[PDB]
Image (cartoon, rainbow over all chains, first blue to last red; front, top):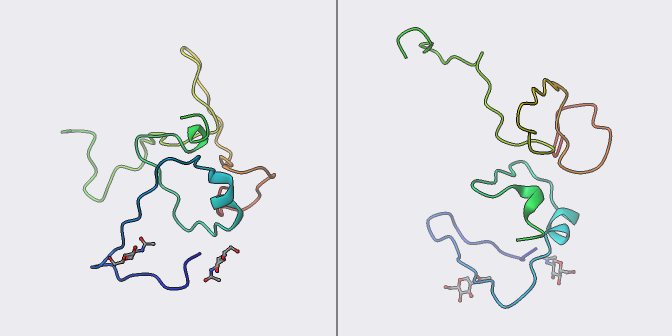
Length: 48
Length: 49
Ligand SMILES: *[C@@H]1O[C@H](CO)[C@@H](O)[C@H](O)[C@H]1NC(C)=O
Ligand SMILES: *[C@@H]1O[C@H](CO)[C@@H](O)[C@H](O)[C@H]1NC(C)=O
């Protein structure tokens, strides 16, 4: 929900560590045109 | 590849990449209805439906 997003050639890399990753928060505001998960099942994101 | 590769793409063979669950061994699931990634009785092909 950032106010401004960086360009594609200057994609911004955010580091996420030392915290619990709650994907339900992401789903709360997700108009997911694309939700493609590779190598990890999306339903198994809450127990890994 | 000689007899199973359509020039425009052989879409008759469907490999399931995401599903509601994981197939039980020796269990042929032919559920052609849409898989729902959320929770609702999805009617049209949309997000999580
Ligand atoms: C996105 O929502 C968060 C949480 O309410 C808020 O802090 C942030 O300012 C919002 N960003 C916007 C509106 O660009
Ligand atoms: C966006 O990029 C700038 C410049 O590299 C960096 O300082 C900032 O932390 C980045 N923001 C996020 C949210 O990753």
